[PDB]
Image (tube, rainbow over the protein chains, first blue to last red):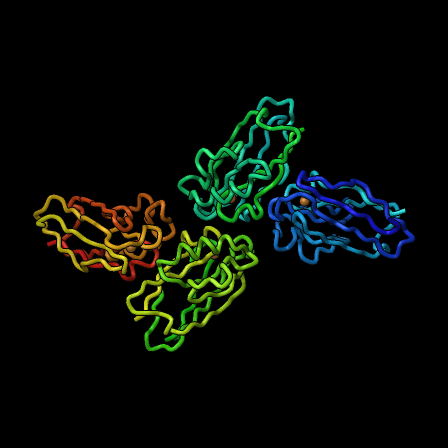
Length: 128
Length: 128
Length: 128
Length: 128
Ligand SMILES: [Cu+2]
Ligand SMILES: [Cu+2]
Ligand SMILES: [Cu+2]
Ligand SMILES: [Cu+2]
């Protein structure tokens, strides 16, 4: 509640939120991702990935090419501020990151990088 | 155009887009597939195949079992909403299908069924 | 040199030889596999896998089902006499196996089990 | 028997002849190929392919690369004087060719172009 959000990615290619605001007074912020539904990771895998709005396209593009065994993320992608693993239905993953990595006024996007998902599974993140 | 999309599958085993939007005010939608590159068709052949997300795995698995002879598609597969032929380098093929075949509340995936290709060659199709 | 062979699998989905001879007077035989080219493992990965001709199809079918994370080989597959790891471009791997595992009168095939690859990446191994 | 020969290719990668002599008084010559054994075409396919000795390596190499659905022969290969289709166990095929295509004094080879078989399955053909 204070410094975390719980997010679900389902079999209908939806996150159950499209907007996050991180309280600047949190030292760290945590996203707890889960995957209701029944489809497997190779058909309906979801991650939660954070970048600047400007970097989203390249993160998604390079991620899609990286393949499932790399969680559809380019390894060591410096544009990725934080991310969960790619999960299938019934799996879960959390990611915690340092709030100092964000700056007020900058535009951030969160999204899933499974091929074709970012067009449907994305939202804004703000720091206040 | 308003009722079609151009898509490329290349010799890096990628499509050049992974998300398609079909405008519900179209009667029909056309996918124009092309194949930049130069590898033989029996090495890097591509098609564009559409099914629901729930059906994708079966279409791909049965498709590979069907062999090159059958363009890696199970003949008269009822799960396949639309598909192009399998093409090699420098070739083109288009498929047109009725938008009435889609519903606003369903999840669709497009993909190549050549063995192993769907690892990267897959994406979403959404009716809006 | 008398008890080993160097073999390459390339970006054209070919091995650079399709017939290997194993000298009966060798106690052990070594295959040194390399991968000229530049495609990544998840597009054009190769291994070198040995079975009887009669087991080849079953090994290839089950290997495909096993996934890239298993190097496209069924775990503990009793039909695989010997195998390298799966490698991408610029990588190499060797396997050594006891020549006593080969029997006179039997027919052997080597092949890559990456999806679709065995179509062209297959060959014979003969004990002399 | 004066203008034909029956040849078997078995599960042991052997033809049952290593040498053919075509009587030049024949207008045409026929090879009747059969495949004793149990193994199917995809792991133990055999064809009977005729070229000059000088052309054999290129025919075999390009044949390999062409795949099972092309009977492991390059389409319209001008170096191929005559060929059967590729057969598996229990199957049969015959080819007839004009004897005028052959020159007395020239060296010819017959062989199977299934990957790795030509090293084991080849012989000479002479016109007299
Ligand atoms: Cu997703
Ligand atoms: Cu493809
Ligand atoms: Cu391979
Ligand atoms: Cu053969």
